[PDB]
Image 1 (cartoon, rainbow, N blue to C red):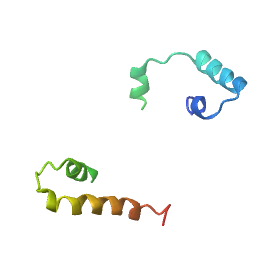
Image 2 (cartoon, helix red, strand yellow; image 1 turned 135 degrees about the vertical axis):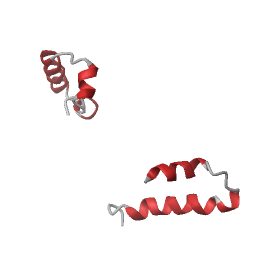
Image 3 (cartoon, rainbow, N blue to C red; image 1 turned 90 degrees about the vertical axis):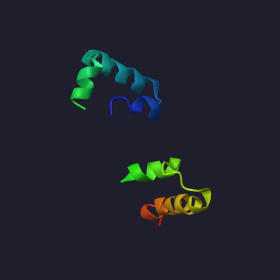
Image 4 (cartoon, rainbow, N blue to C red; image 1 turned 60 degrees about the vertical axis):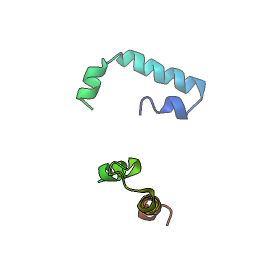
Length: 76
């Protein structure tokens, strides 16, 4: 949330204040930043790892496309 405002909010004073905050806190080395922190088969279907013939391939991809919008409740 410190960095998100740099690409969303644009008012110059706000950005100067944000970077000032970052500087005062100051340069955490990324290692500690990381320390503090199924679609797999469908992904292989997107590449056809199983080497299916194209005829039995279009149904799978069209289906996964339809399920992608059908699962999301935001646009029902």
